[PDB]
Length: 129
Ligand code: NA
Ligand code: NA
Ligand SMILES: [Rh+]
Ligand SMILES: [Rh+]
Image 1 (spheres, protein in one colour):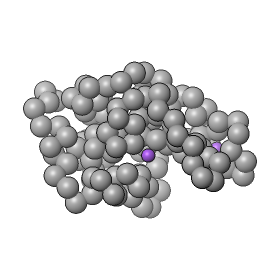
Image 2 (image 1 turned 120 degrees about the vertical axis):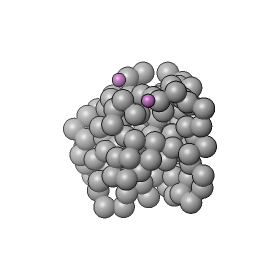
Image 3 (image 1 turned 180 degrees about the vertical axis):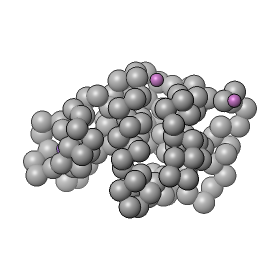
Image 4 (image 1 turned 180 degrees about the horizontal axis):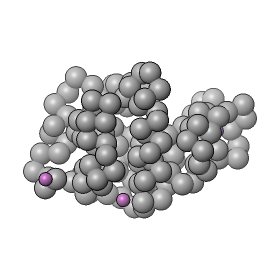
């Protein structure tokens, strides 16, 4: 599923991301924009052999099992394919574990490089929430 901006903002708010660990909803929308272009089916291979999955590009090195990432963890206790669903529940719940892991949203290099220190409120401007 390719979400609209405000549709994704509403779905993330309902699933409890707004101000989760102090990160305003605009931070999560901005991260999703630059990670996946709001596409739940997005996948990308990493140099280490792991793969990033879904709307927030969650990694098989630590967070999910994709059956092909050797010497990895599955800390969200899910198949990586769950992160590609039109239903973002698994990606949200797994993102809450990731953002709680010590580095906050710096876990998403796209957030650090494209969203941190910017006017992220712009990502939810105009949305009915
Ligand atoms: Na990415
Ligand atoms: Na894994
Ligand atoms: Rh939902
Ligand atoms: Rh509201």
